[PDB]
Image (tube, rainbow over all chains, first blue to last red; front, side, top):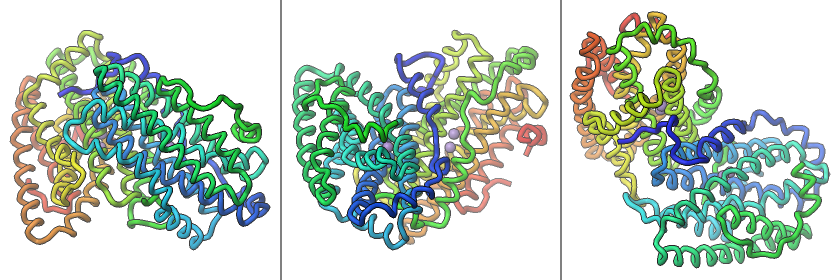
Length: 288
Length: 285
Ligand SMILES: [Mn+2]
Ligand SMILES: [Mn+2]
Ligand SMILES: [Mn+2]
Ligand SMILES: [Mn+2]
């Protein structure tokens, strides 16, 4: 039985990603958010509700990535150095999830926070989104998995945090770019800095697995990947309509979703499928 | 589907352990090992070989804990806050494993290091040890597991890092307690500091599951736990004889194994089953 040996490279990238993930390590106590209260109260009830709902959804995604996605993918990887990187990434998903609770403790009462998490747990589209993604992870709950199954779980993982999440990162970035909730915006930018390299790394692993497949299996997962992309896109358009109609941002959020879907495809070595638009300039200022 | 909500406690201890795990965070590059060369060369060939072999075995343990044990236990937990703690622990197991390579890079040539890892991969006792432990984890690769299966995986985890690899920490601590290889000893102490709280935490989770089992299931896992304890002990006794006879430390290491087996039992809320070396104790300072 093999032990991980870092003095002999198993690939050309795992060490670099290990060092980068460790270098970027942070926790929620590093950013004080109390100063956001002054701009929080300047928002409308509908704006506050949208903010809490999108952060509720982000918490769900990170809960599933740290608790199902990364662990089940990494268990089936044979590269021990890449496994190490995924374990660290999985830990950071739990830091991400906890940091949203750090924001909530400042911006909401205990009753209001209970309301958020109850709404998350019962929401039909969130359940549908999460259910489709985690079904790919659940297929890995067996002693031996096929590379097709492992590839598609990697695709699901890239789509979750390079793509599906951004319907949610939009609004904290949009507000931060307008000078509102900027401390919470600093936290969201730390999360995005992590997820950027999470998606690149998993996409590299996926491309390596894809190249190992038979031609028949490659054709199957190529088609399944494109179907999944557009299945999730249809659900995300319904979600954006539900969350953002009240505050007049549906089409803006949809453009951001398409932008990040193209990024997820490129992380997988695949061509863009949506027209190449510029990032919303207010969002861009929030990423600064 | 539920998201983790840290503003409402799911238990009375997960936050306490989250904060402590975080507070103890460290990486392999914090301790420079170069100064150990001066005491390394003063060891005999037999002492150097034993050192490299024990550290190879420790690496295997952490490779298995971070890549199999922690992920498969955590994926079946219902408590999302406890899940979070275990995910962080699993990440630290990879820090542990990488830190042994950091030591090797200073103390061994490239060819010698590849010899170590070849010896680890083909060693029959290490294969048997790891195979017994990871068979409890492999049982968790299915969509529905029983609480007996999850309990026994937690038992195996506690035994792995409260018990079954102290046959290995003995020698780094023994040398460090004599002023030899003290920088590597500092790394081992950071690892032990983590593993102390890993075993306690998984032991708490195990006791919580145990209390939900029927009386019949409790009887059955109690028997399996005591038999596993002694199956591993027999293998460990053979391992210590193989590793330490050349340097005259078999009986000392065996005493240390029994002491830590008792600690693993206590982490599970169980009574001790066996009736510390003072130089090892000085290496823990
Ligand atoms: Mn994340
Ligand atoms: Mn991620
Ligand atoms: Mn460890
Ligand atoms: Mn451990």
